[PDB]
Amino acid sequence: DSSRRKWNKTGHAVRAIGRLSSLENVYIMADKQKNGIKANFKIRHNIEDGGVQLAYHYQQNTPIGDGPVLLPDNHYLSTQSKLSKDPNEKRDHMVLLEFVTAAGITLGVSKGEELFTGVVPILVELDGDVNGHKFSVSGEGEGDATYGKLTLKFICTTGKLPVPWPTLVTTLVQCFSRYPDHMKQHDFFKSAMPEGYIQERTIFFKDDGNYKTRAEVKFEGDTLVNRIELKGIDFKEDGNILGHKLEYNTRDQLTEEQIAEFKEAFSLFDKDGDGTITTKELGTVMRSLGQNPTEAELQDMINEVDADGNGTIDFPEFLTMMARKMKDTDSEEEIREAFRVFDKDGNGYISAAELRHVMTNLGEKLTDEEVDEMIREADIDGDGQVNYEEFVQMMTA
Ligand SMILES: [Ca+2]
Ligand SMILES: [Ca+2]
Ligand SMILES: [Ca+2]
Ligand SMILES: [Ca+2]
């Protein structure tokens, strides 16, 4: 099927631009008034059987001790988590593997960091109360900040956890993040150790309640300990949280067929075939789709996924951002936005002339018959056009 592969390539390009235009990282900034930092970010929780539950986080951290700390320039953390189960464990539990790296400062170490050069034991204790449903969680494992690596197992010590495990991941030690060499002066978290910091958040679950958390993170002997209280209010008993409607298992697939699909979209951008995407190349493709980014906007889009800070999107960086984009689910607003890239006139239907316009602009030399074949592959009800629902099915993996 040459039609379905043209949909895939084009769809992945639109999806790539979507990711580049989104803010998916953990954004950190100095909070001078508190001698610390604040942060904001959003988490996408896959809903079982379809859709996304958004969780908007606001965070602030303040040192526990009076020693000097590092106040960072603006930057972000980028995370990769894998949730699993221990087959021998009968209690309600979560096994967590996590890698976290700082970035967001283009190219061109505190005493506290010394405590993190090797493997450090971790303890986590959480008491929670969500809509009056109380619970406790205890966790243990270790952190290896050299690689930004955490391995932890958590148990609900009160029996059944009344909220989905994924909703507690962000609450359950950012001092283990890997900061690159050129960003070591921006690592507040380690700079506050061993005395530690207080971390507070409010977490807004869209169309549902919110969590309020306060935690003390500090060394107790040789162990890095995170002690947390969590209070949730305003939840719907039958919502995605209290109703346990969120996926547990990390959907970190990535067939080699999918990686190949990603590479095809990569090469639409990488038109000189040197294995990296520049602002110039990104701008070219966006304009072809009817957009008009400034140079500053293009730099910012690249910076959002530019792991090594060299100002371009390298092939491995592109694979990484696309993996994240496919792992997580897009919102209805985001999908409709992609739909509108094709549905130029906004009547709810992608016509042959509209599809032709897009493919032609992307430099895809396609005959009028080829376009027709594309429409047909997607045209479910047979009306000779592609409606939202049919577009969605073409875009879903
Ligand atoms: Ca290139
Ligand atoms: Ca790069
Ligand atoms: Ca239309
Ligand atoms: Ca149709």
Image (cartoon, rainbow, N blue to C red):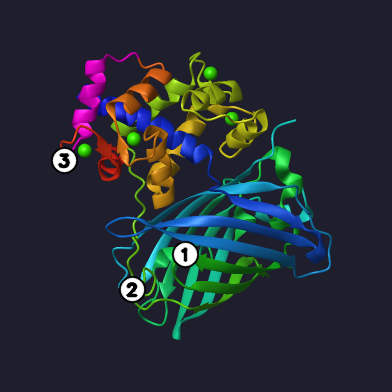
The residue where tag 2 is placed is 243
Does residue 206 belong to the magenta stretch? no
Does residue 366 belong to the magenta stretch? yes
State which tag comes first along the sequence, 2 or 1: 1
Q: Residue furthest left?
A: 382
Which secondary structure type mostly characterizes the magenta part of the structure?
A: helix
The residue located at (81%, 60%) in the rendering is 32
Residue 306 visible at all: no
Where residue 381 is drawn, which disc sits there? Answer: 3
Left or right: 392, with 117 as reference point = left
Residue 380 visible at all: yes
Q: Secondary structure at mark 3?
A: loop
Q: How far from the left and from the top, in percent, is residue 372? A: 22, 23
**Where, by quadrant of the figure, is residue 322 drawn?**
top left
**Quarter of the rendered structure image containing ligand 4:** top left
Front tag of 2 and 1:
1
Q: Residues within 10 Å of mark 3 (few under 14, many from 20)?
A: few
The residue located at (41%, 67%) in the rendering is 165
Q: Secondary structure at mark 1?
A: loop
The amino acid sitting under disc 3 is Asp
The residue where tag 1 is placed is 206
Give the magenta part as a residue range. Answer: 365-380
State which tag comes first along the sequence, 3 or 1: 1
The amino acid sitting under disc 1 is Lys
Q: Secondary structure at mark 2?
A: loop
The amino acid sitting under disc 2 is Gly
